[PDB]
Image: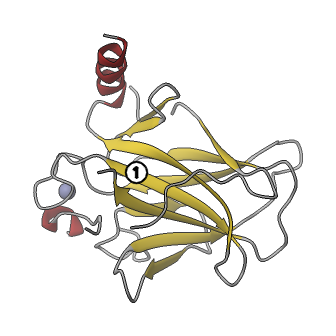
Amino acid sequence: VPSQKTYQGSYGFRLGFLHSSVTCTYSPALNKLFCQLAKTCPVQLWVDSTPPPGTRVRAMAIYKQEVVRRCPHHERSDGLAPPQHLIRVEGNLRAEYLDDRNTFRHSVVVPYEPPEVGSDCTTIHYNYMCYSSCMGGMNRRPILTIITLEDSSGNLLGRDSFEVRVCACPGRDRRTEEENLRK
Ligand SMILES: [Zn+2]
């Protein structure tokens, strides 16, 4: 099972989020992102110092409590992300879709890019292609997205993660879960 241990590492790597009708909303209290199917999910990459050129950013989904993949229905597109992949990157011409030869787990990698002239963090846009409730897919089991900062050889430089619930009413479900957390 892929490690989900938070690791800021030498560059002080950690994630930040943005609220995007609600299509995407993040709960700091639950460290959980609630999002609609296939909509833009802005995830920010924050570092204290800039990693070396050739640095890469990998996103992978795992069950919080077995490979995470789309249910048969949602496998059926940009012609880049394999139909079985739950996580897709939006607006990046250099996304690589990978399947581990040993664990069969899917992941999508993009080159790490320093913040834009004026901005303090790097934003990557992700899309989740199947619902948390999908039978034959996640079937209501909670999942986690693990983001790893890596060197050109795949060595770990940093790691952060967040739970994700892909659902039809992100704002409503976030409120329900936070209220219940409070309860
Ligand atoms: Zn599905």
Q: Secondary structure at mark 1?
A: strand
Residue 61, image x and y in percent?
40, 60
What residue do we see at 33% from left, 50% from top? Answer: 64
Q: Residue at x 41, y 46 (%)?
A: 39
Residue type, mark 1 in image: Leu
Q: Quadrant of ligand 1?
A: bottom left
In this figure, which colouring scheme has been used for the structure? Answer: secondary structure
Question: Where is 166 relative to 108, above or below?
Answer: above
Tell how many labels.
1
Which residue lies most toward the bottom here? 101
x, y percent for residue 156? 66, 70
Q: Is residue 51 left or right of residue 150?
A: right
Place of residue 75 in the rendered image (x, y in percent of width and height, measured from the top left): 22, 69
Q: Residue at x 44, y 36 (%)?
A: 32
Residue 150: quarter of image = bottom right
In the image, 150 versus 2, the foreground residue is 2
- How many residues crowd around disc 1 within 10 Å: few (fewer than 14), some, or many (20 or more)? many
Quadrant hosting residue 81: bottom left
